[PDB]
Length: 89
Length: 75
Image (cartoon, rainbow over all chains, first blue to last red):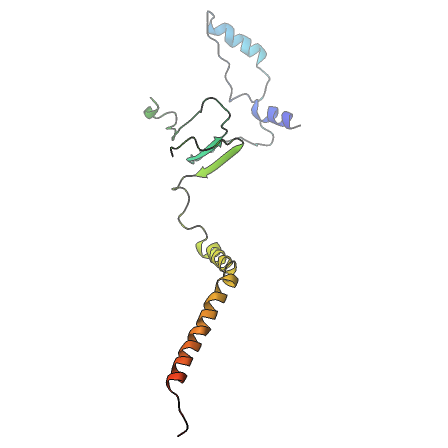
């Protein structure tokens, strides 16, 4: 039931992309997508729209002391800039 | 003593948070005051019976000083 809820709430038409790359023309792809993807979705279960929340970066450390290992892994990280800003580049 | 060859530890995850995003004094007058009263409960039963016994001996010592230096005979 939860699987069917997830399938219902996130396999929706407008959010998703069909894209092809290779030696083929756009008309063929558009017509085949018209003949097959006409009829997936477009409306939610009583408008239960999933929506992003811009979350918060905490900054902390979790250290898993486990000495019976040959090498040690460290990951250090800071804030992400985002996408559309050129600070990305 | 260097730093790194002290012991062998497995099976332990230590979480900890940054100093900035937590506050200075979390519930300072809310938990620290029962904290110090509990600490005082753990000690005074076996701290005070030296000191009050010392104190009564101090009072008695000054008492013997005054009453044995000031004599009041019969004459």
